[PDB]
Image 1 (tube, rainbow, N blue to C red):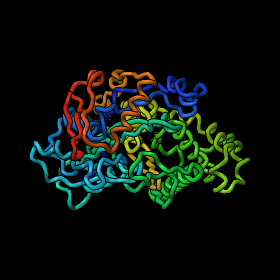
Image 2: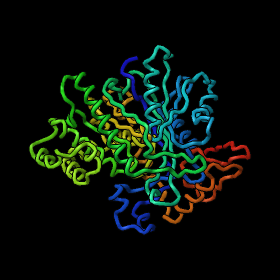
Image 3: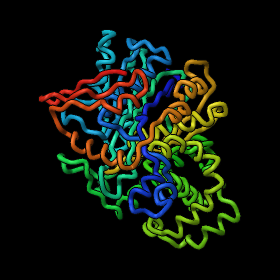
Image 4: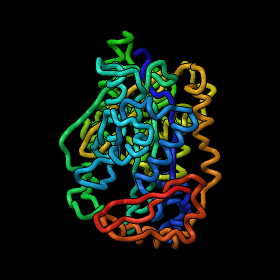
Length: 450
């Protein structure tokens, strides 16, 4: 199996959304608190008719369909999600209905979990499966799916929902540079969900910033070390064409890329020019511990990174800014944004990906993009995903109707024995979309289509 990586991708997000500007006004918030301070424009959200299962159905069926993939040709199916539906029965098992109809039940894979990192863990397991002695010559299929918008509180504007499906196989247009990565994992209580009966997390804002930056620095350092062994030169921001990040909100993306410039400063890397050096020098006496909480450092790193950001990062932001936090699918939606925006110039380029999940688990890994024939080509991936079209076909909710919907979702969370209400909503879903009809008295969920 040569050149293993991503062959095909498709993406689903709910058409129902709320504009961040309007939400600012609805809340008691000063203008631009969300659109500038978070860097977020719009928030897609599941109504009562949509959930992680239904969104996965849309994305996988669309992928299978538009790339003309025989479902019998899937040898492994894996799911990343932090959205808990059952404590025992995996989301993977639900998705198997989509293969049973073909009689394809000999399929490896289950669910991977750690916060926003589960989709990455699955992706890597699937790539490793293709390269392994156990590979049977069939495709791997990875699903990242998540939905959560807190009905109340300060975290409500940072919600979102999507499912991404990725077909994995040899001879790919998107190739894993297998040795060029670094991971960081640790036992921390930065952000976790310890109360099984509620969606509210315990958050330690203090620890969480320290944890995320520590993971990012550490992944970058490990990847740089690997690069130095591989290519015999020190890595800098100049050695990749694009940097793609886990993108819960856009401001964190800006800070993340800027932190990489600071790292380059510390390593006296060649991305750091004359003037940049002089900008960072006042901060050369800061300890690492000190570096994580310095606002002044943040702003200078931001000033330095500014020009590189528009070239290397900005094209990865379309979907996350228009949809919101997609949790496990976030990084892959940023990547999908990149393909949408730059497909005709991506052949030959290096793309660095950074995946994070609180608790904490993180990996920075590198991809090389390649010219390939359709249907497994960058151009055909951009065409199939139709991100432009999906964005044009959205339906805006007033913040009012949005808040009522979130209260409704709060009511249906971990609940049994109800029928969803289709009146006014089904009209908004595109033709062929899966939706939740009812959850019976034994918590069993039933779906329709269209």
